Image: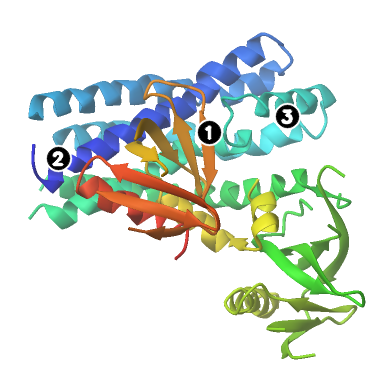
């Protein structure tokens, strides 16, 4: 074909091909590492897997339907299977129950904790294990994004799919946010030492690097502003918390005694130096808005002096885009995955092991070929189409520089 409509189907199939590959990190890869141990209680094993395997055996049947229509071309398949997913919503409502359960067992069974982490260190678990339990619900969003873009292009059946998906996703908007802020709350507690942070009435705002001022000089420390408490590190294996600063009620003002600002709390007060001008201006609004309302990416941020928000996290999720393109410096052809604001390189399509991974924080996008410039490391990327070159920068530029 030779138009923007057909090119969409490629994006769908190519991102569906990795979606299944993510389920195969559970219905396949995590499955065998469970049956080999028999260490997971039959109460939990019959709670995570029964709600997951049908997703694979269906979306594989979806994939055989769409890729078939691709081969015929060189619409209806959407509304057909989208109407079919409605017989899967029940499973998706049991995901939040699972993620909460998968942590109550790690907080008790020391075997499960020592094993789950040991599984996370496998080279198929390219993302933290918890995030894989969300993918069945994330594929709901990226179906909306595709079917919306069709209702913009085409000048009747696509209108049914964007209507069906919306009502569906907006109904699953319940768990998709509860367990959304649950994961990045729990995973944060796996990188922070000296806390012992899972309060039911607690949310996550943002985190990042802010060169804290001290009597000595300036000291770059990590800052994790939560709903109620902003806490910070002290620079062994993980990040050792220094002190806490309960928000309500504190006063934050600008300063001159370095492009910075102070934070006078009702208890203790500290002076924080920003990384830029809009690193301050970003941190300020996130802080005061969490004060007024009160009435890993960690190592990447720390090592590059940038901040990441829940506001930011949901952005690099709506901007998930997998597919093929070519890469070389001053061509290698490889299957490339974009997820959690990070690049992932694969040898070929049907792999299950990342060749390498490019952390896209601080990288600048410039110029069917774009270029990801950063400090000294410079990469060139040639996309395989005209729409896929637009769509590639579409997700990258929105996750990298702006």
**Callout 1: SS:** strand
In terms of image quadrants, where is residue 284? Answer: bottom right
Tell me the CA gap for discs 3 and 1: 21 Å
Which of these two is toward me, 316 or 362?
Answer: 362
Say left or right for 123 vs 329.
Answer: right
Counting from the top left corner in percent of width and height, residue 239 is at 81, 51
Counting from the top left corner in percent of width and height, residue 1 is at 8, 36
The residue lying furthest to the bottom in this view is 256
Tell me the CA gap for discs 3 and 2: 42 Å
Q: Residue at x 66, y 72 (%)?
A: 275
**Callout 2: SS:** helix
Q: Residue at x 33, y 55 (%)?
A: 394
State which mark lies toward you, 1 or 2: 1
Which of these two is toward me, 172 or 203?
Answer: 203
Q: Residue at x 76, y 47 (%)?
A: 189
Instruction: Kindly identify which residue carries mark 2.
Output: 6
Q: Which mark is residue 117?
A: 3
Instruction: Kindly identify which residue carries mark 1.
Output: 356
Can you see residue 162?
no
Badge 1 crowding class, 10 Å Cα cut-off, few under 14, some 14 to 19, many 20 or more, is few
Tell me the CA gap for discs 1 and 2: 30 Å
The residue lying furthest to the top in this view is 36
Badge 2 crowding class, 10 Å Cα cut-off, few under 14, some 14 to 19, many 20 or more, is few
First-in-chain label (3 vs 1): 3
Q: Residue at x 22, y 44 (%)?
A: 161
Residue 91 versus residue 24 in the image, above or below: below
Counting from the top left corner in percent of width and height, residue 123 is at 60, 25
Counting from the top left corner in percent of width and height, residue 369 is at 29, 49
First-in-chain label (1 vs 2): 2
Q: Which mark is residue 142?
A: none
């Amino acid at each position: 074909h030779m138009d923007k409509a057909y090119f969409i189907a490629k994006e769908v199939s190519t991102t569906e091909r990795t979606y299944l590959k993510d389920l195969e990190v559970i219905t396949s890869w995590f499955q065998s590492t469970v049956s080999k141990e028999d260490a997971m209680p039959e109460a939990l094993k019959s709670l995570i897997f029964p709600n997951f395997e049908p997703l694979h055996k269906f979306h594989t049947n979806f994939l055989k339907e769409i890729e078939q229509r691709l081969a015929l071309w060189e619409g209806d398949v959407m509304l057909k299977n989208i109407q079919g997913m409605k017989h899967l919503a029940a499973h998706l409502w049991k995901h939040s129950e699972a993620l909460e359960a998968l942590e109550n067992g790690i907080k008790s069974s020391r075997r499960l904790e020592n094993f789950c982490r040991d599984f996370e260190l496998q080279k198929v678990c390219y993302l933290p294990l918890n995030t894989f339990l969300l993918r069945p619900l994330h594929r709901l969003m990226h179906y909306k994004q595709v079917l919306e873009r069709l209702c913009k292009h085409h000048p009747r059946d696509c209108r049914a799919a964007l209507a069906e998906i919306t009502e569906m996703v907006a109904q699953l908007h319940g768990t998709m946010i509860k367990m959304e802020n649950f994961q990045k709350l729990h995973e944060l507690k796996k990188d922070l030492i000296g806390i012992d942070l899972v309060v039911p009435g607690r949310e996550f705002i943002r985190l990042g690097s802010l060169s804290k001022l001290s009597g000595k000089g300036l000291q770059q420390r990590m800052f994790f502003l939560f709903n109620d408490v902003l806490l910070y590190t002290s620079r062994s294996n993980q990040f050792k918390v220094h002190g806490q600063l309960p928000l309500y009620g504190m006063t934050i003002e600008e300063s001159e005694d370095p492009h910075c600002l102070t934070l006078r709390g009702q208890r203790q007060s500290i002076i924080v130096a920003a990384s830029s001008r809009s690193e301050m201006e970003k941190w300020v609004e996130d802080i005061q808005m969490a004060i007024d309302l009160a009435e890993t990416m960690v190592h990447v941020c720390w090592h590059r002096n940038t901040s990441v928000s829940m506001v930011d996290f949901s952005i690099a999720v709506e901007n998930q885009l997998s597919g093929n393109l070519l890469r070389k410096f001053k061509w290698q052809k490889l299957w490339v995955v974009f997820t959690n604001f990070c690049l992932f390189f694969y040898k070929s399509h049907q792999d299950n092991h990342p060749l390498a991974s490019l952390p896209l924080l601080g990288y600048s996008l410039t110029i069917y070929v774009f270029k990801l410039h950063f400090k000294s490391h410079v990469y060139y990327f040639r996309a395989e189409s005209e729409y896929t070159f637009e769509r590639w920068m579409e997700v990258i530029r929105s996750a990298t520089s702006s």
